[PDB]
Length: 415
Ligand SMILES: [Mg+2]
Image 1 (cartoon, rainbow, N blue to C red):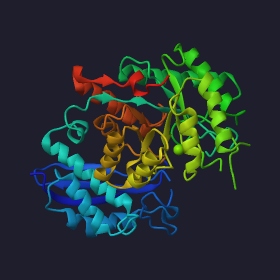
Image 2 (image 1 turned 90 degrees about the vertical axis):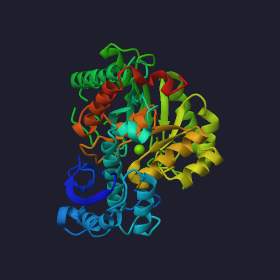
Image 3 (image 1 turned 120 degrees about the vertical axis):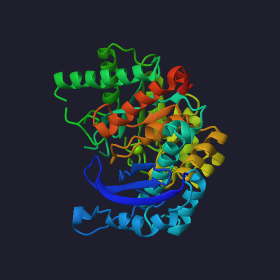
Image 4 (image 1 turned 90 degrees about the horizontal axis):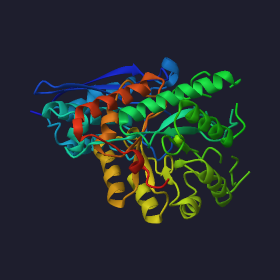
């Protein structure tokens, strides 16, 4: 059966080197799955990691979340069937007791949520992406690679994340190759120039501004042998609630900023702009929607905080046209898939994302295909807690045989 027998937890370290929560579920059929949770630390609206505090691991201890698993979650889940993800995830949700998943920790609750679905697919003999996404799920996603980290990670280049997106590629296999080829070209470009140590997501680091970034990457694309736009597009997370009394800096206002964007949108082949105009600045979103609505994809990172209540409002109130999907924000798979399915009933595009503190876990690879997002943001072809998702996506495409199809240009309609 898909009947949960054991649920044990471990304290392990993420890509930053900071404790997180590893959950090991045993199904009665014999299945034993691993799953790891990534902090990547924010907001009140996001779920609340149960961290230790104290001087152990600089307050970043996860012992309580672990003990929380073995003491309470484990016995609460043990004996149920993994194959009722909605029922397990609700059961986990209640047992906690709060809005913020504060009491049992969202790090511990997702960890249980995910180690279930892993076992619930190795039960059924379904690769994770098939099982969770059924069998029509065959869309290998455009890799949105964050080659250059920026302001908020020097606030000199105010943009946070500068992304290569190989929409032109005939396959995911090729799309991976381009990205790596071009990341390695930009290594070359910046090596020759004074500008090459790595950032938290494998992204490279002073800089003149937004234009310098673009100017740099355009050249890297050309240097790699690819044409910008047709082969490799470009995209960014501004994280504009880092620029911010009225707080735009890049000095600009929301409507004034929409023009800054409009400028970039004309010359540089932008496929998607992430978290422009703050998180709570609803007015800015409607103006940005009005201004660049159908020339660029506009995606909500911190605005929507992967929470359906806020995205509903944004969709109803017409903020953005696509959502960034962070599983650890929301805390459960079922709640996460609801996020996807709400947005897909509504028709916002999906972009499954990582966090800055990642693990060797590659579930986001499978998850992204299963939801057929057509887009995955999982970092530069560099740190292996980035690359392992990419390799995983190799294998899935391998697995899919002729069934596979690479989102590519139909990932982003506007170009
Ligand atoms: Mg961001």
